[PDB]
Length: 361
Ligand SMILES: Nc1ncnc2c1ncn2[C@@H]1O[C@H](COP(=O)(O)OP(=O)(O)OC[C@@H]2C[C@@H](O)CN2)[C@@H](O)[C@H]1O
Ligand SMILES: [Cl-]
Ligand SMILES: [Mg+2]
Ligand SMILES: [Mg+2]
Image (tube, rainbow, N blue to C red):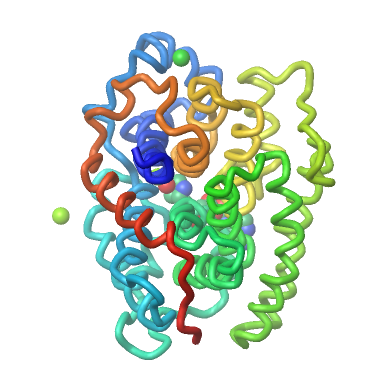
């Protein structure tokens, strides 16, 4: 109602529901173990009993809305110069809404360094500690804005530059690429088993952009292999490297096995905390879950890692594909910023549903 638009609304609202559920007002951090989280989940009456009335969204939704609101304000056929001004401004400004929302170090530090308005004032230098998932968690709606094939170059550039406004490390900003790219694939009903291959094919194009852009190319290139290698390895493991083949999951892949797997994906032991593994876990959830919100939630919202970020990503992708089908109303009806999220979604659809261009840098 319209069917196109319904998917956009769900992408935005269920991304935020995911964040809130995966955050639980920071309480999951005192457990930091999927089995312990799943048992506390049971004692709250399970997923369908959860009322998000008092479950605040975290930094993930706040920053996702900032992306979305910037895209919307940029309008039809924007100067990429204006879009980057607006993304910087929205990111910097949204830092005022992080009370009790546990934002990340790179997100905060860098958003506060930006100089929106000044030519190139939204660029920061390369940094070794900037491979967190703070760019990936907020980039999905770039794929809603720019879903058409003709726009791939835009999606690549915008996802990367939105990302490296806070995360100028390929592990960071390629997270944003994957987040946006897969949202675009979901918009276009591209079956999820093809998404990984798609990303592996676009990484050389992302590299060509980073190279022509001319910023810290030496450093960017030298760290480039970590992301790529982790994704190759993961798609190999799941048997979807060829992108024609349905995924293979282990016989034994319950809550406990998922935690250990998420830890093996991680940079330094914390599943989904980085730009490579946050979208990877969301992707793994989406591939297992099909049309089940409960399944997606048990895999992407409730685990011992950065479940808020994995949930934000997975909930967006999943909502694009499946709308609100099978979702308990208590899980989103009183979700913080629901009206705001619906309104931005509608506005993103207006733009996204029209195959326009950008005025280049
Ligand atoms: N170069 C790196 N490669 C892989 N991971 C890295 C790299 N540099 C930093 N990280 C990891 O990224 C994790 C999160 O980074 P931060 O800068 O603290 O957080 P940020 O990415 O801004 O936000 C992450 C959000 C914050 C919460 O919503 C949970 N997820 C850190 O604990 C690091 O372990
Ligand atoms: Cl449950
Ligand atoms: Mg968060
Ligand atoms: Mg205040």
